[PDB]
Every structure is written in C-alpha cells, then in structure tokens.
C-alpha cells in the first residue's frame, strides 16, 4: 500500500491533541427546561443523526448510527437499539466508525439519561483503517 498512510498516523499529533478522553455533550436547547432530557433523547433517537461536540474544543462531529429515516414517511417510533442500552447502565450512548479526510477513526461518546455532559474517547485504531485506506482509492 502507499506509505503515506502509516506516515501521517505516526507523525500527526492531531490524535493525542483531540483523539483522547474528552468531555462531550449532545447538541440541544439547554435553555429548554430539563424536559429536553427525555423528549430530546426520544425525538433524537428516532433521527439517529446526533450532533455532538467536545466542550474542551469548539470542534464538532456529526454522526449517524441507526436513524428511523430522513425524508421517509414512516412512524414516529424511536430506535429500539437506543432503549436496549438505556435500560442497562441507565445511560444512552452511540458508537460508529466515521472517516475524516484520512482514514476511519472510532467515535463512541456516552451520556446519562438526565445530564447530557458525558465523556467520549476518540482514537484512530480501526482495523478497517489499514485495509480501507488501501481500498480507499477507486
């Protein structure tokens, strides 16, 4: 494979500077009474298109795990997968492999059902990164 893959990963410090354990919070109207904790979780769960950012950095990452549908006229039913992990630790979290202008990195933030100011570690360690980088070319 082209050696420009391993090279950027071993010399780019951008991983430790931001791809590390950082505080995270879901994007929503905090000025909306605590009522957003439940309504935002369910209404956002149907649209699994969560927007979230790192409190430490103004950086923001958008991601999509299993959303009911974009323009679909389906039902307003939520993502069963979201409540199959809400009953467990009593928290709601998502994990997905997103690619940036480089290779795949694993993003998996978590937050409790009431305070949406959890933590989320981000790190370049996807095994699909080494092979997808090779197959990244058309």
Image (tube, rainbow, N blue to C red):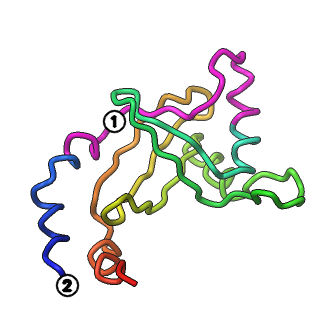
The vertical placement of 7 against 71, above or below, is below
Q: Position of residue 121 (x, y in %)?
A: 34, 45
Helix, strand or loop at mark 2: loop
Q: Nearer the viewer, residue 62 or 80?
A: 62
Quadrant the N terminus occupies: bottom left
Q: Position of residue 73 (x, y in %)?
A: 89, 59
Q: Give the class, few, some or many, for how many residues have Cα within 10 Å of label 2's Cα (few <14, many ≥20).
A: few
Q: Which residues are magenta?
A: 16-40
Residue drawn at point x = 72 percent, y = 16 percent: 33
Q: Nearer the viewer, residue 25 or 89?
A: 25
Question: Is 24 contained in the magenta span?
Answer: yes
Left or right of residue 94, residue 58 in this image: left
Question: Is 77 contained in the magenta span?
Answer: no
Is disc 1 in contact with disc 2, using a CB cutoff of under 8 Å? no
Q: CA distance from mark 1 to mark 2?
A: 33 Å
Q: Position of residue 56 (x, y in %)?
A: 34, 27
Labels 1 and 2: the sequence-earlier one: 2
Quadrant the C terminus occupies: bottom left
Q: Position of residue 28 (x, y in %)?
A: 63, 29
Residue drawn at point x = 19 percent, y = 45 percent: 16
Q: Nearer the viewer, residue 38 or 56?
A: 56
Q: Which mark is residue 22?
A: 1
Q: Give the class, few, some or many, for how many residues have Cα within 10 Å of label 1's Cα (few <14, many ≥20).
A: some
Marks 1, 2: nearer the viewer? 2
Residue drawn at point x = 13 percent, y = 76 percent: 3
What residue is shown with label 2? 1
Identify the residue at the far front of this view. 138
Instruction: Please identify the quarter of the rendering in which residue 57 is found.
Output: top left
């Amino acid at each position: 494979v082209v050696p420009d893959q391993r090279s950027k990963f071993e010399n780019e410090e951008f991983f430790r500077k931001l791809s590390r354990e950082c505080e995270i919070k879901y994007t929503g109207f905090r000025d909306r009474p605590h009522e957003e904790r439940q309504t935002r979780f369910q209404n956002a769960c149907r649209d699994g298109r969560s927007e979230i950012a790192f409190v430490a950095t103004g950086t923001n990452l958008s991601l999509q795990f299993f959303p009911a549908s974009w323009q679909g006229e389906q039902r307003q039913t939520p993502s069963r997968e979201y409540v199959d992990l809400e009953r467990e630790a009593g928290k709601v979290y998502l994990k997905a492999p997103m690619i940036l202008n480089g290779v795949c990195v694993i993003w998996k933030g978590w937050i409790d059902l009431h305070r949406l100011d959890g933590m989320g570690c981000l790190e370049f360690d996807e095994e699909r990164a080494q092979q997808e980088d090779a197959l990244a070319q058309q």
